[PDB]
Image: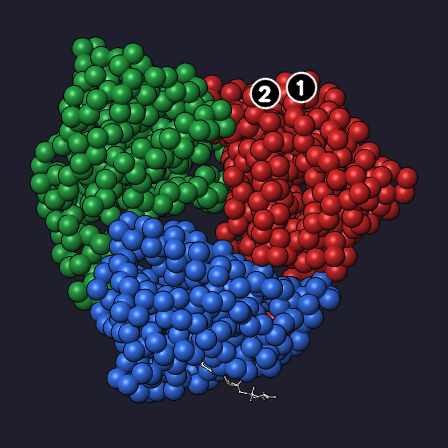
Chain colours: A blue, B red, C green
């Protein structure tokens, strides 16, 4: 049995060893919980974004950045892979814990979800849960959580607060852009499960996605970071048994395709948890089926929409 | 003073510390030999694949995976380089030792070849021999080696079985796919030797090759993994003195070029013998000549053949 | 505070633990200075080139090599990024220390610059100074510095020669080619400062640049290594506030744009420090402005000129 919280805790300790280099800052609160700021009152960095992504994926994914071009324009890209896709993506990475503690609101991702069982149905579906006495959570938020928030997280995870760590970054920050593009494989796995495909059948997944420039506020950044995956995110997946249903994985099969994610976000009143989950999906996928030995390709890339989404200005 | 077996054993010790994360399993046999299953009864992983390949190359190469596209279809690629191409590729990685013990048969690669000296003529040519009390072999096989097999290998290496490690994966497995595409530099070096170009003249090489999808059995996989290099493997090589014979390195200069290996092999009725050996070669190379300061490009890529080989189904 | 010398010294100690693997050679001089030959009487290596580049950037950058193609011709590329672009690129990397000790000439780069403050105006512009009592310099030179040269460097940095390290490689060497393409982010940051843009406004930068083949002498190599960046170097940059003057960052906005830099190296008398500093610029940039949330793209790639600089011979 692997422990995503223990593996991720090792990465968080590495992050804390290099705080100044990574442009992050931590604080131990009055109950002993550790809050790591990766973007609210600090700049963060590409490497902090990679480490935050690795932590969200329970330490069970490789994540790196390579610079490449789209129609000759240079971007940083995330390239990543995992051989524990259900656990890394659904059991850890997905932001499946909505944190609401009086006026404090955050989207919660990462290994702590596998202790608190958030949501319970996910852990039934992937047949995984952790048992650790350390909890590691990743918060997408424009404010840092206080003692009361950390005490609530600790309680839900059945751990002491002194054994809770939270990484925190806002949507519009470099760590935000990196970690959200770092969910490229997770988008595919999540969309596959939403359409009824058993994620326990998925053997491995590898993905690439450009890293959104940082737009002027958290709301517009929600749009462009998500469009990175929807219009320009590519996944190679290996599965035990193919299902014709997987033709409906790519975003271009959605009635909302062509729309800026910012549009969809606005209609949900800027509440991420009011977005229809059936809308998150990768631009393109290739699915290697171990049963037939065939590889089925679905989807397409769309630089035109992406450059609109990224507020690119050409000469 | 570089020991490919000592360096490789350190990598194998790492693989042992992370078995469950890598999805591999090890057994210590009655004679003490350690057999590490990287794909027979276990799924393996992309990282087990990279480490397997690093082991094959004696620890003297960098090997990593990046996700990229071919005609927009996503694949995982190996990207690799070495500054010891003779030792890493000829003295270690090449599957140059046919292991035949009763009815057990496997192609052996990796550092143990440099203790067994298999074949002797290679070690004379590259002016390398290892001197070590530990042997690390990598076996491409559908069955794990038992006590008697490991005793045989240890005898041939002159090491006590207690100090022999074998990594094992079948041709159709993720480790199989990764480690075979991870021979992209080795196929250039080996083809260069084959056509009469002294490997001692070769300074370094750096290569890129897509990782084949896993096909439905070892024989089809033998085809697709090899076609990765023959139809879509690229190598940049640096040499002390270029000779025009090197125009013959690319696989496209073989009389047998043009169909997927498995179909060529079908056409030879499973007969190694009746296929031009010059077919085993990279798709394209660029050769930086240190003498003239020119860089000579030969060969081409072939996505059309690659996609037949990979049994790609487009919509 | 981040000490570029203390961090870089750790990289050099790592290089000293793997000399034979990296194909480098070190000597401790009489005064205790450690001279690491990375390319003068030894071959060096791609990995030695990456570590030399990392040391030039003060350990404050990520540097890796990926193999990819330009018009299908395979090359090794540097992919790199930093979140301390003023410190790493201008405070450390730029070769801003002209070394002239009797008959010994070298271009000096690297963290020792931030101890000797060379040139002073740079340290005033970026507001950085180091306080280490170790010094690490990178010399681009075709001969190894002796006891007297290292005495001069140690004195200028206010450190005992026993605590000084020098890395040394000529322009025509693998370490030369890697390290110079490894300045792709720095070329953008330097040009930005040149045209009056405060480098303190620069949040981060990420770049890709092909690694030049080694040409037949240091003079031709000065041309092709530099053309890598000027004709095929791409940079993604983040800044706090955009300024329209940044439209003049790309090399193609210079009067002299269009011919290989080999013609330009002569029209400065083969003196690097005689070259007009406004020609020294990246091929293409994307500038993400945090204020407006827009990303402005300028410049263009030029494979045709690159293949000429590189002395590519196609069939
Ligand atoms: C790409 C996304 N973007 C994004 N952006 C930013 N800025 N930050 C992020 O963290 C992030 N996401 C990461 O989390 C990404 C995303 C993939 N993750 C995500 C999405 C939604 C949620 C919320 C939620 O709980 C989620 O909707 C839920 O887990 C599943 O969704 C619903 O759909 C299903 C409906 O049930 P069915 O009708 O399928 O029932 C079937 C029948 C099938 C049918 O015919 O419909 C049955 O029971 O037989 C249910 O399981 C129900 O839970 C959480 C994470």
Dot 2: element: helix
The label shown at residue B200 is: 2
Density class for disc 1 (Cα within 10 Å; few <14, some 14-19, many ≥20) is some
Protein chain holding label 1: B
Q: Earlier in the sequence, mark 2 or mark 1?
A: 1
Q: Residue B165: give x, y in percent of width and height.
A: 70, 39
Per the image, the residue denoted by label 1 is B125
In the rendered image, residue A153, in percent from the top left (x then y), is placed at 38, 76
Percent across and percent down for residue C211 are 40, 36
Residue C277's spot in the image, x, y percent? 17, 34
Q: Residue at x 27, y 74 (%)?
A: A146
In terms of image quadrants, where is residue B196? top right
- For the residues labelled 2 and 1, say whether their Cβ atoms are less than 8 Å apart: yes
**SS type, badge 1:** helix
Q: What distance separates the C-alpha of mark 2 from that of mark 1?
A: 8 Å
In the image, residue A49 sits, relative to residue B299, either above or below, namely below
Q: Residue at x 18, y 14 (%)?
A: C101
Judge by depth and name the residue closer to the eye, C98 or A284.
C98
B246, A219: nearer the viewer: A219
Q: Which chain carries label 2?
A: B
Res B236 visible: yes
Identified at 15% across, 59% down, the residue is: C241
Label 2 crowd (10 A; few <14 / some 14-19 / many >=20): some
| Location of the N terminus of chain B (image quadrant) | top right
């Amino acid at each position: 049995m692997l422990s995503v919280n223990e593996i991720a805790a090792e990465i968080v300790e590495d992050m804390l060893d290099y705080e100044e280099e990574l442009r992050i800052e931590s604080k131990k609160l009055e109950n002993g919980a550790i809050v790591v700021d990766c973007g609210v009152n600090v700049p963060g960095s590409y490497d902090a974004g990679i480490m935050y992504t690795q932590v969200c994926m329970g330490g069970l994914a490789d994540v790196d950045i390579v610079v490449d071009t789209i129609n000759d324009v240079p971007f940083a890209f995330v390239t990543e892979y995992t051989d524990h896709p259900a656990i890394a993506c659904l059991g850890s990475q997905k932001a499946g814990w909505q944190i609401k503690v009086d006026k404090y609101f955050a989207m919660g991702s990462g290994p702590a979800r596998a202790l608190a069982l958030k949501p319970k149905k996910t852990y039934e579906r992937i047949e995984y849960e952790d048992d650790a006495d350390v909890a590691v959570i990743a918060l997408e938020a424009n404010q840092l959580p206080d003692e009361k928030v950390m005490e609530f997280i600790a309680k839900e995870c059945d751990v002491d607060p002194e054994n809770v760590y939270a990484l925190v970054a806002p949507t519009a920050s470099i760590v935000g852009s990196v970690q959200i593009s770092g969910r490229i494989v997770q988008t595919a796995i999540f969309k596959m499960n939403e359409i009824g495909y058993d994620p326990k059948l998925i053997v491995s997944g590898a993905g690439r996605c450009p890293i959104s420039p940082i737009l002027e506020n958290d709301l517009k950044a929600m749009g462009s970071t998500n469009d990175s995956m929807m219009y320009y995110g590519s996944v190679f997946l290996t599965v035990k048994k193919y299902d014709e249903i997987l033709k409906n994985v790519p975003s271009c099969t959605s009635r909302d395709y062509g729309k800026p994610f910012y549009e969809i976000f606005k209609a949900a009143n800027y509440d991420f948890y009011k977005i229809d989950p059936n809308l998150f999906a990768p631009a393109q996928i290739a699915v290697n089926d171990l049963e037939t030995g065939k590889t089925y390709v679905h989807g397409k890339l769309n630089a035109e929409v992406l450059f609109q989404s990224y507020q690119i200005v050409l000469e």
